[PDB]
Image 1 (cartoon, one colour):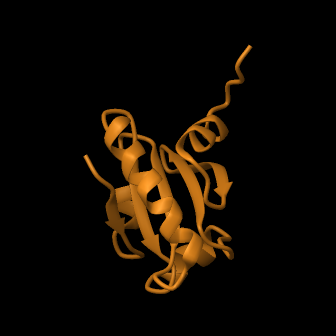
Image 2 (spheres, helix red, strand yellow; image 1 turned 120 degrees about the vertical axis):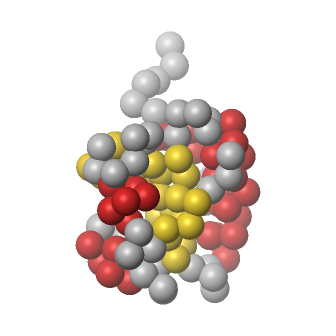
Length: 108
């Protein structure tokens, strides 16, 4: 299980209508930190594949979707559930940090 590529044209069917929650990576080809987070996302997409879809949205090819979700900086991740944006992550970080930030739980 790897990431999927999505676009303005496919966002409704492939992100909003997804059965699984979808973590959408808003990125661009010229973007340095985007490159650092890409392998973390592929790892998560594999390890959590039965429970999570990870989608990539090139904001330069799809500026309509970026505008619609108020994504200005990149890399920005937005977690969608049942069509609804529920959480945003800003910036490149390691897998442990990212999963903990995504979580609504805290360790005791």
